[PDB]
Image (spheres, coloured by chain):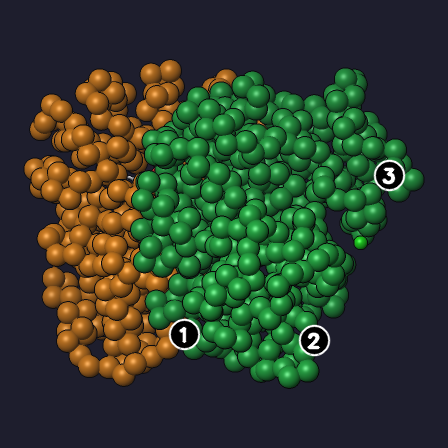
Chain colours: A green, B orange
Amino acid sequence: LTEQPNWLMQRAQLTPERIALIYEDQTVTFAELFAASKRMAEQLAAHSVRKGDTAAILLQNRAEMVYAVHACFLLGVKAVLLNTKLSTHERLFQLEDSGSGFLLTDSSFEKKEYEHIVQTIDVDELMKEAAEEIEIEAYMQMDATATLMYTSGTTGKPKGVQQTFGNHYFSAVSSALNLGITEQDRWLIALPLFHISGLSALFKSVIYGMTVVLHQRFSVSDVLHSINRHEVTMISAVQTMLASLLEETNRCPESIRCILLGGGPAPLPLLEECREKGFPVFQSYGMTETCSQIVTLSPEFSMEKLGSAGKPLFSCEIKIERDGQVCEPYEHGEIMVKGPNVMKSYFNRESANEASFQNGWLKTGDLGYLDNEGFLYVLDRRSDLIISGGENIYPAEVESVLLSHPAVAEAGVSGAEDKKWGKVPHAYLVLHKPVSAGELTDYCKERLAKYKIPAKFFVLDRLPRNASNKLLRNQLKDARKGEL
Amino acid sequence: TEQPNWLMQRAQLTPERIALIYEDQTVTFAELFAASKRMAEQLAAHSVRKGDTAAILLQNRAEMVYAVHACFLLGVKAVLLNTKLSTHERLFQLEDSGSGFLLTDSSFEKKEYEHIVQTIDVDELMKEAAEEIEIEAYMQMDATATLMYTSGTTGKPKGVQQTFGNHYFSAVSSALNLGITEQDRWLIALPLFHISGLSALFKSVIYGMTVVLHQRFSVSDVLHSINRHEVTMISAVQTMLASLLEETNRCPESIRCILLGGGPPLPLLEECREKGFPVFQSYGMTETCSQIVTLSPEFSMEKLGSAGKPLFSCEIKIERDGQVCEPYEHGEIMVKGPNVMKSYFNRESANEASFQNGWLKTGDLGYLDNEGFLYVLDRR
Ligand SMILES: Nc1ncnc2c1ncn2[C@@H]1O[C@H](COP(=O)(O)OC(=O)CCC(=O)c2ccccc2C(=O)O)[C@@H](O)[C@H]1O
Ligand SMILES: [N]C1=N[C]=NC2=C1N=[C]N2[C]1O[C]([C]OP([O])(=O)/O=C(\[O])[C][C]C(=O)C2=C(C([O])=O)[C]=[C][C]=[C]2)[C]([O])[C]1[O]
Ligand SMILES: [Cl-]
Ligand SMILES: [Cl-]
Ligand SMILES: [Cl-]
Ligand SMILES: [Cl-]
Ligand SMILES: [Mg+2]
């Protein structure tokens, strides 16, 4: 079991002089990281931040933010990670809903807009203060909520995912049983730390005793220099980052032994060149609810199983279900997951919890299927499913064939009411060059069943997205002009 | 509170990975699961039901590995019996453990146990046809997986109840300590009824790692097996380490870790650190389901003859007269962690005497230096 020694505390005790964090070319050892985090904890403690409270963190990727997360752990305070791209309204909603009483942030955000709800605290000025030394929380309770992270689904109001210390621990372990651990391993994070893809590395770090090379943002050149300067072996990335890394290099940096690719679907041709040029890409499937990846695939299988998300990590389980009955191979249904990395429950979401759980299994809201060998193929969100005359239209499928076209930069497919059929597919595009709708229909013709092809076409400057750049399909109708 | 069966899931993930090398045949994990499922079905035919306790009296064989897993797949507590013990020593443990069955073979005399347990000849058992059964696809973390008896003086042997959870966290903690590599293969010439050997079987299904298995230790045999199968991890006691040093000058380049367990010695370590042998000194016991403290080779000159530091998730402290001991101040070593045993089987007195607030009094003595390294002395 029910408790473990604090990960950072014990890691500092075991290997004090291992590098914990590399940011901006400055280095921080685990002993230093613990000292910093303990110091920040004591400084927070002087602001009436008591054990059992809830603190929200609104920060860009800095070394200070790493301190803040650990400081909350050492104080025994639930850390709420806030997406920095949220509107003032969205931030306030999550602040209130989470029951945060504090907001750790800096001068780059308008802290004054939230004083009326929570006690705001500037990180840089907090560290300039003096404080009475406190005795930290030396033990993490495995079933205690460590961090609260909000879902970014395009359906309904965002839910707070309760991630336990146990969840994070088993995420780190399962991943390591899958990827292996060397003493020379170093992980580069250019993804935000308020997202689970970035946050989880901080826990991998102290549990493995592994150095995290931290970047505030992703630039291909800064990353490539960083990889070579620090002998980076592990890197986490989304599709666009991987695509950009291929444009700027012929060969993959020898130092890199793993590229954990997640967050969504990757186009087959992109993966095919990674195979070609020796990029060790690990396709993965996971969510905030699962504390990161829960299903991963090995470069050995990328061609063989190109479109596949892989198999469950050790200790983890997946199944495909439809109307309560388990699906046959290739039979489409809802992806359900299970394992010690799966969240406790959504915070303060009675309806969502009851509905999303069935006998210890989590309904992910994702549609997909398994092949004969059990490899997972993710399809699309169920909520975004389009029915055209009894037939199922997965927007991600049509968006993919549209995206593959050169003149098409962004594609969005939505279900519009039709008389002849239940709904009809509509394509909302952003374009690099102009494309004739004839050449476009003649492009979808060779790649899609007739009913899948978008009846009409629209053109825009941008597509409706939330703070996670996820496409808001229900808001597509409408923003702008459409030609034929 | 539960994980899918390690062997079953491992077989699902990487079916074709070698699970076992029992020279010189090979068993894939898919094969290991198939063999272990068959033996389970054959045992059920002998009225071996879930919740029962079965004793295993075998020496290092592929069939012994199947037997352990067959118990897990059946939901049967496995008692691993030391073959070097006398007959009355095993009879005591059979009575004590509450075993209903004894799995063994021709090398041991059945009907020298039949008057106390129902005996089954594993080799005979395998030849028999049996109906299919639905295996126990889940391991409960808090349920007793194996029962191993304390082979030590100062009292009648106690049965250590080792949970599936204990074994898992054992395997994980050592991984966090030693690291896992795709090309890793562990060599076990130690007896499988001792936790030093048994734990490797669990590392195998959890890591997805090949175990090269020997019956006994013979230095020439081990070195040939090391190079033929490219062993990278080796478990050994000092007698084995002194032998391998007294045979060849150069350490096989394939080996990356030599996990030394049991007692000390000090002059022998220098002969390894200078000869290129990556020896890892460790402090562990049946109670802690293997090692709980290991010592990295890089800090062996500075740490002299130290046990090392606790594995991740694990804790050690030194106590005397109920109070904590300062650095270098002697006292009893006390361990704590998810790899530490729940309780002795049917030993209420020993349980209360040995456990104080989730801490296990080891019955051993030692201290910690300024840098927190464990230096171990002796038993009471
Ligand atoms: N592989 C794949 N295919 C298709 N759809 C996919 C997908 N992976 C995720 N998804 C969809 O995104 C939803 C989950 O999004 P979030 O809840 O906000 O969190 C994540 O995306 C987890 C990804 C992640 O953690 C990551 C990202 C980048 C590099 C590494 C890692 C990592 O696992 O550590 C979900 O609903 C699903 O439909
Ligand atoms: N190191 C040391 N030192 C001193 N002492 C000791 C040590 N170690 C141990 N020790 C002792 O002994 C005992 C215990 O015993 P048992 O329980 O019976 O068993 C054991 O030991 C275990 C070990 C192991 O496991 C091994 C390994 C691992 O870890 O894995 C490897 C190899 C070998 C072995 C106690 O009591 C103490 O005291
Ligand atoms: Cl809102
Ligand atoms: Cl390591
Ligand atoms: Cl459906
Ligand atoms: Cl252990
Ligand atoms: Mg498992």
Residue shown at 25%/77% (left/top)?
Answer: B42
The tag on residue A329 is: 1
Ligand 3 neighbours mark 3 (CB distance < 8 Å): no
User: Callout 3, which amino acid?
Assistant: Tyr
Please indicate whether residue A416 sits to the left or right of residue A272 in the image.
Answer: right
Does A35 sit above or below residue B258?
Answer: above
Please indicate whether residue A411 sits to the left or right of residue B36 in the image.
Answer: right
Disc 1 is placed on an element classified as loop
Q: Are marks 1 and 2 on the same chain?
A: yes
The image quadrant where one finds the C terminus of chain A is bottom right
Q: Earlier in the sequence, mark 3 or mark 2?
A: 3
Residue A361 placed where, x, y %? 56, 67
- In 3D space, how far apart are the residues under numbered discs 3 and 2 (Cα atoms)? 42 Å
Q: Which of marks 1 and 2 is nearer the N terminus?
A: 1
Label 2: how many Cα within 10 Å (few below 14, some 14–19, many 20+):
few
- In 3D space, how far apart are the residues under numbered discs 1 and 3 (Cα atoms)? 51 Å
Q: Are marks 3 and 2 on the same chain?
A: yes
Query: Can you tell which of label 1 and label 2 is closer to the viewer?
Result: 2
Chain hosting mark 2: A
According to the picture, the residue beneath numbered tag 3 turns out to be: A114
Q: Are marks 1 and 3 on the same chain?
A: yes
The tag on residue A417 is: 2
